[PDB]
Image (spheres, coloured by chain):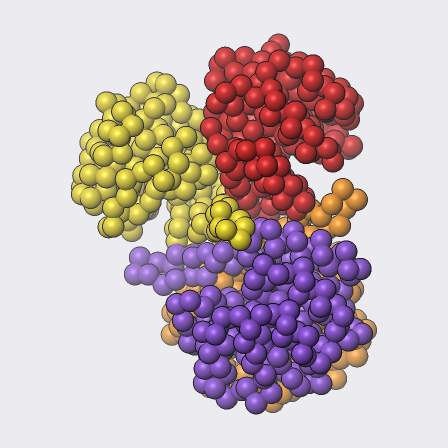
Chain colours: A purple, B orange, C red, D yellow
Amino acid sequence: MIPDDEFIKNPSVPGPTAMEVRCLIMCLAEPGKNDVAVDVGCGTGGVTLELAGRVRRVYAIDRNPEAISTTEMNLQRHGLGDNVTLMEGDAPEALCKIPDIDIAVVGGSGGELQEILRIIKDKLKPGGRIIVTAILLETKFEAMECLRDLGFDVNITELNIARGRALDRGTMMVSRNPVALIYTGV
Amino acid sequence: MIPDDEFIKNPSVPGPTAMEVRCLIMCLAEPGKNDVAVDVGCGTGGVTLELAGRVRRVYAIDRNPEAISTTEMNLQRHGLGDNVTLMEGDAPEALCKIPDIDIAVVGGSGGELQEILRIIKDKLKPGGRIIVTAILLETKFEAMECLRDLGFDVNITELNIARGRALDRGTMMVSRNPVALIYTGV
Amino acid sequence: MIPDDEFIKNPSVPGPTAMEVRCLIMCLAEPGKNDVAVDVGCGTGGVTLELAGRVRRVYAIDRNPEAISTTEMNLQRHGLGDNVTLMEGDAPEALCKIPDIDIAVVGGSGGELQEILRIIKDKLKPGGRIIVTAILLETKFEAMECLRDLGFDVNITELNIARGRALDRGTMMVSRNPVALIYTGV
Amino acid sequence: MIPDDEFIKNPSVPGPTAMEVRCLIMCLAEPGKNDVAVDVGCGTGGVTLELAGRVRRVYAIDRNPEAISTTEMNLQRHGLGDNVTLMEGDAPEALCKIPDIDIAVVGGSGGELQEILRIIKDKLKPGGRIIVTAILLETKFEAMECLRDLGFDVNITELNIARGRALDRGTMMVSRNPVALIYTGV
């Protein structure tokens, strides 16, 4: 999989999602070659890149123009993007213009999490999966609550990752901020 | 991916490796359909199962007969194993009888880690990858050291995973023991 | 400090709080010899024992009779308890019958967290401290929210602890479930 | 206890040790008012400050002059230091010039960990305690090994701490790098 260091970064754009998290998102999503996926809040394009090479169509959404731009660049550098529809603008509006989906990954909730999830529920193909990426303590709670209130069986996994950094004196373990994945049953 | 609960367990056999770890091993291994892989210390068969459905040939090794047996069962229950060669007996001896490999995953080091790694280095095809699973503090150190002394560029990632358990009162987070992955460059 | 293994346990009573957590609670509480403290949901008595030997008076509350019982026992085995008032029954009622407090530690929220916190706010002596122990994801959120809505400056710290277990083959790290401490400014 | 933010920091000097770690070091050390303690690799002075206000004498050692300097400053700002002997220079040499000790905390091993521990073993008063702070993977291993080879019963505890950071959108959990504490029996 593409490591964090091989991504094009931008100051106003957060990400990429740590590779270890992207790895788990892919496993929970269970991407099929005929699946249609949406990535709400694509940021640097980490999740978009991985999905792109595994499903039929990927719709990448973000309010931040810089994010659409960075995702666009990372897509090209790795020769993907032919099956990716980039969409700038407000998440709720953009989601209304999209076909039904098999996989929905919601990163930057952008405050409108509850609305985004309701909309996503109305477009979810049977057997579809929703995966919410949470950095804020409130998102972990809000996501769990919404998904349960929309009738899904909800689960949550928190990851704490430490990678070794080679120093002269030795290998020191460097932490990544904890990331929680709230996901609905398959 | 196959979740931990859908595996056939045995008392004298450890595992399965937590799904989140198996997920990362697969990502680091970058399994190609024409790759030959070896799984030293296959245990319950977690890694063997995942590799089986993605590479050309998998050689699963373990000293413990119960492990070969459990791996065998889990393979059957999921309709895999046609491309898996099970091998009971001492790791170093078994490795000498195997073709050259593209991917090597070393779980249960079984004390002979240093020797196993040397042997694996002599059979690694160019561009091959080695991934060592460490539970013991000594294995983390020893693996790092050996691989470096064998001339590889070594990395290490520690994972701390917590999964939510639905209780009546609410969702409590339950921890998994930390697991470290020591891996060589691609 | 008293280690987890030197506590008398009971089936229906959770605890003791991991020593590493009890250690941080004591540090955040800043127990003075003339302070009056309340321990809501005392469980096995871990926090009660530590406070007992450092403040003037400790009021230990729990609905579960077994818990009051276990706390009672652990208090005796360590020769403390002269300055501890045990109180069985519903937390909100019991809190109404107690003097004003300098330190309040709330363990087993027992569903009535919001009410317990309001009450505790009305009895808090100036410069007092509140520390909420959270195991459930909802308690972390609810505590943060209540305390903020009651006008306190709120903080949160999550601890993930692993202790080494000496095995014949080596030292394996064993995890404790994550525990969060939500506390108000001093 | 003194929070991380109330310390004077310096570029070339690492620390302060996270408060949650300092809290546990104090608990493992069990500082008595008549104890003599040594802090090898005092850095910003975190451990030195805490020990200062609890034992009879504290000998703070560090090769880095800037560290001695920073510790000196933090001591003053909190009105401590009357019972602290600062010592610049190479750890092994400095330790030879100190009285026997009750408590020894070794932070910045500075490569000479093995020698430092040997020396410390020869000056440890009966019932004395040694606590080694490890950031590097190699130190965790080396400390465990040395202390065992010097005849102590060794233990290890790894802490992963996350603190909440109030943002407008909510409270995001921010991680601290993992820290291991290797300590000998009391």
Task: Using the image as rendered, state which of residue A120 and residue A134 is in the foreground.
Answer: A120
The answer, for residue D124, to whether it is visible in the render is no
Looking at the image, which residue is at 49% across and 70% down?
Answer: A64
Vertical order, A6 against D166 (above or below):
below
Spot the residue most to the top: C82
Q: Residue at x 40, y 50 (%)?
A: D135
In which quadrant of the rendered view does residue C90 lie?
top right
Q: Is residue D57 left or right of residue B158?
A: left
Q: Nearer the viewer, residue B27 or C155?
A: C155
Is A102 on the left-hand or right-hand side of D5? right
Q: Nearer the viewer, residue A139 or D176?
A: A139
In the rendered image, the quadrant that contains the C terminus of chain A is bottom right
Q: Residue at x 45, y 77 (%)?
A: A70
Q: Quadrant of residue C87?
A: top right
How many numbered dots are placed on residues in this image? 0
Viewer-nearest residue: A110 or B105: A110
Instruction: Using the rendered image of the protein, determine whether residue D82 is visible from the camera's viewpoint.
Output: yes
**Going 38% across and 59% down the picture, which residue do you hit?**
A171
Position of residue C160 measured from the top left corner of the image (x, y, whole percent): 55, 46
Q: Position of residue B163 (x, y in %)?
A: 67, 54
Q: Position of residue A14 (x, y in %)?
A: 47, 66
Q: Position of residue C148 (x, y in %)?
A: 56, 37
Position above or below: B109 against D181: below
